[PDB]
Image (spheres, rainbow, N blue to C red):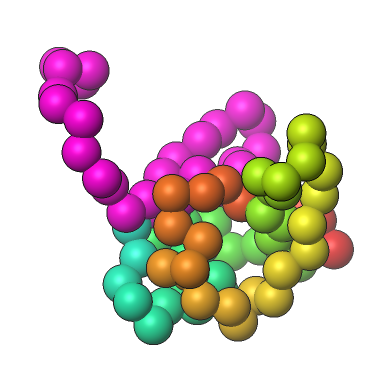
């Protein structure tokens, strides 16, 4: 029984999963991006070879921004990320 809650601040980010799949994750202060995929993957147990993340620019219309995998996950909270092969 989803959809039906007041407006509140939730610490979660949108990760891009292949096959049109989408899942949000909550991170603790001092967390890294490498860890941001641990919570989403923990549920499916899928071990990939190479993955890369990109955060979308909120200043322009819709560009691509390369970020570090060891970057603070709580710093990109409420935003969206995108991972690709190699």
Q: Nearer the viewer, residue 85 or 35?
A: 35
Q: Nearer the viewer, residue 13 or 57?
A: 57
Above or below — where is 61 with respect to 27? above
In the rendered image, the residue lying farthest to the front is 59
**Left or right: residue 27 compared with residue 14:** left
Inspect this view and state whether residue 44 appears. no
Residue drawn at 35 percent across, 65 percent down: 27
Residue drawn at 20 percent across, 38 percent down: 8
**Left or right: residue 9 compared with residue 76:** left
| Residue 69: x %, y % from top left | 65, 75
Above or below — where is 28 with respect to 2? below
| Residue 38: x %, y % from top left | 45, 66
Q: Quadrant of residue 74?
A: bottom left
Magenta stretch, main secondary structure, is loop
Q: Quadrant of residue 11?
A: bottom left
Above or below — where is 44 with respect to 61? below
- Quadrant, the N terminus: top left
Q: Nearer the viewer, residue 7 or 18?
A: 7
Residue drawn at 27 percent across, 47 percent down: 10
Number of on-image labels: 0
What's drawn in magenta, residue-wise? 1-25
| Residue 5: x %, y % from top left | 14, 24
Q: Nearer the viewer, residue 4 or 40?
A: 4
| Residue 82: x %, y % from top left | 67, 49
Q: Is 46 a magenta residue?
A: no
Inspect this view and state whether residue 29 appears. yes
Above or below — where is 20 with respect to 44? above
**Left or right: residue 5 compared with residue 38:** left
- Quadrant, the C terminus: bottom right
């Amino acid at each position: 029984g989803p959809l039906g809650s007041p407006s509140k601040t939730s610490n979660t980010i949108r990760v891009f999963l292949p096959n049109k799949q989408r899942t949000v994750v909550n991170v603790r202060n001092g967390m890294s991006l490498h860890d941001c995929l641990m919570k989403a993957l923990k549920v499916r147990g899928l071990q990939p070879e190479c993955c890369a993340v990109f955060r979308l620019l909120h200043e322009h219309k819709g560009k691509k921004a390369r970020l570090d995998w060891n970057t603070d996950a709580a710093s990109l909270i409420g935003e969206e990320l995108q991972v690709d092969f190699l």
